[PDB]
Image 1 (tube, rainbow, N blue to C red):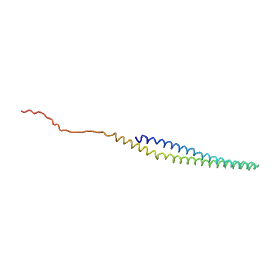
Image 2: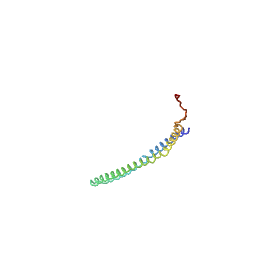
Image 3: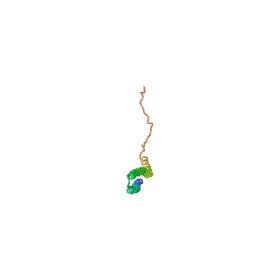
Image 4: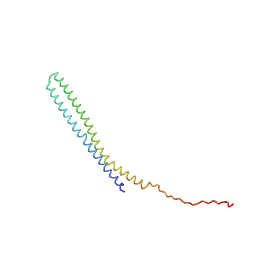
Length: 146
């Protein structure tokens, strides 16, 4: 009568873990939604630049050069966004490392008091009680008188 209800407080801890992971996950990839939007908008800026340049080109060599430049710019955008994918991976891994490892912090004590009550009960149980005595009751054998 102690651990009876002390063990119940872990549910608050479990729900809090869920809430923290919950709000991290909602926050994560949301900032990354915004980052993907920013990269798509910079790419749209590049696309607008090249479309205006091609519209004003009116020459075959200029058009081909602008095609090559647009290809190069899209490739640079893709490389930067791949580095960004690495960044999402690394950020999210760090976030999980930080927020999870908060789990052990108060998980390990509860388990420890669990061992405490366990071995206290074993103390109250494991006795192997005994009761001993000795005595010196002599043994007699009759002897022939002859």
